[PDB]
Length: 49
Length: 56
DNA sequence: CGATCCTCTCGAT
RNA sequence: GAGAGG
Image (cartoon, rainbow over all chains, first blue to last red; front, side):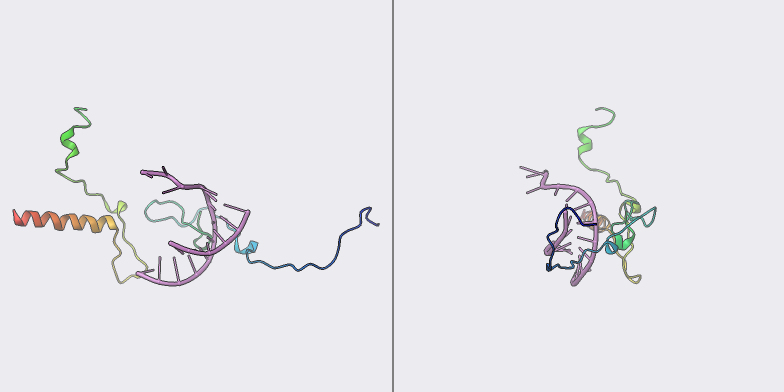
């Protein structure tokens, strides 16, 4: 069925930026602890909290 | 406070030596040391204290 | 003696 | 330390 509204449609130059979910997802349920503070480590790369 | 704080206690006669969990080691390469600044400074104060003990 | 938060990556000592 | 993200 036809849409009641007519849509503005045509080509537009789009850019694929870096920043992709899969490079950002992070989860921690216990893991490596810092030596001094005995607190979770920092950063996704180190399985941080 | 007669019990907890006296002004004679604001001057240091005996300095408390912190344990290793306060100033820990461990590096990136297991061939060299890797000490804490606090440890290096305490070694520095000792060098200064033995020097004073010698001279006296 | 203060000077947003949190998050990432990088290189170099 | 710099470069960045909201």
